[PDB]
Length: 120
Length: 126
DNA sequence: CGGATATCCG
DNA sequence: CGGATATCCG
Image (cartoon, rainbow over the protein chains, first blue to last red):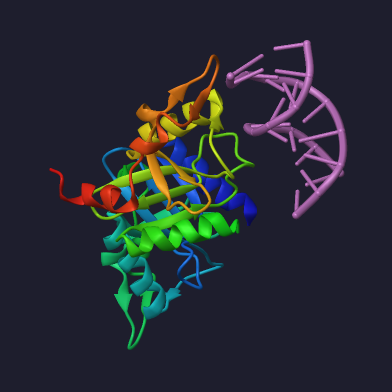
């Protein structure tokens, strides 16, 4: 829980990123994203999710907010997803699938996600 | 809160930055700034300070950690200082005055600080 | 958020 | 070295 978020930051740090947890932006009612990270070359805006199983559903609003932040900041928008017994896995927002009104990572997308080492 | 960070976040947003306050910005063993901001081309790591009057003293450790973070992340390190009845002013770490063991912003340096519009203007540098 | 000590400026 | 401030830690 708190455990796996610590694990995610420690993995990012070991991969060479300085990474911070976000408290807020002072202008929006919601804190976005969850983590921002940079290594001097690559910058990441990360929405962090844990799920007991697939699929992960994301609202259109939450994907829009993440993409808008990433564009305004100069970062790559990512979703980090933790499943039980699995390592953290990273999905560029471009990998998300659409539902009628929203977004998802289902069984067909999950295998395409990246290990932190590849993101670097 | 603080209400100071909040007010600075609003000014950064008005100046075209996507800015965020850093959480657990004291309880961590690793270096981390108060605010991190980007506008698509410029990246800032900012230590935020409010004082009734000059000088602002800054510890060697606080400045070293700010520089270390900014180097690892890929950002420019700045101190943001608010004095009563003055707008926020931004100081690149290279601009800080030195005391015997630490750092400060005092009467000689305060006038050289940048207004938020000049920081935002870095967008157009190559 | 605030009380008390360690640091340290001048 | 005296007193202002950074910092710790409940």
